[PDB]
Image (cartoon, rainbow, N blue to C red):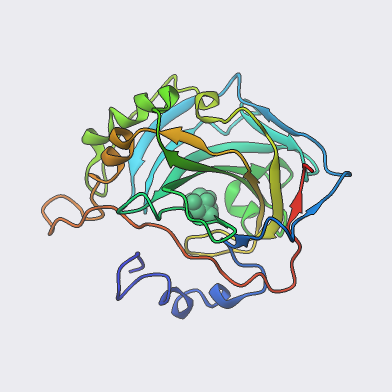
Length: 257
Ligand SMILES: [N]S(=O)(=O)[C][C][C][C+2]1234B567B89%10B%11%12%13B85%14B%1158B%12%11%15B%139%12B%1061B%12%112[C+]5%153B%14874
Ligand SMILES: [Zn+2]
């Protein structure tokens, strides 16, 4: 039932998923002046050399690129994390225009889009078990601004015409997610949740300070995706972002001064 529209969007989700009003919901606004530099935080370790992408999929909340998570091939460690987190998939959230689309905001600034690389804690064995734990998932969030093209995104862009409508997938092997990362691994971190149903409070968020630049042509191709299935009335897949939620009793920590 849930989506991003007037009658099924974020303001409705709490009816099916009451944790939507919980104590550690995501996304949030990152107030840069309030976030505290924490010298005890470690550099983030992103080890994607052996990543094995499998498929690209439209699921009617985004498109995702899925990875083989049956071994420690593409793992996130260090930073605020204890233990090892396997990359399952990445996906994006984006807007109808360049002034909105991100889920996290920075001093209330919205970016054109936000990339999420979703990882789960190997100590829970599978992602379904991991979502039931407060330290089950680590999501690496990366902001997208519009300017110069991101060459490492183009392979993704070019297959989106083949997964237009909900239910469509394609082979998407040999994709290297290192090509989506900014130079700096400077980050903010806080305890939060999935930003889609089931909104489980299972995520350590790691949001990079440095955005990547993508071209207008690249983001335009995101906006040609459809929320609907083939044969149903066409609804452009745009504005698939949850707004910032109350910070409540949480501290956002910065890895950098
Ligand atoms: N925007 S987000 O918080 O990264 C949630 C992405 C969708 C998920 B949630 B957890 B399991 B549940 B299933 B898998 B895992 B995360 B990916 C899909 B959905
Ligand atoms: Zn997401």
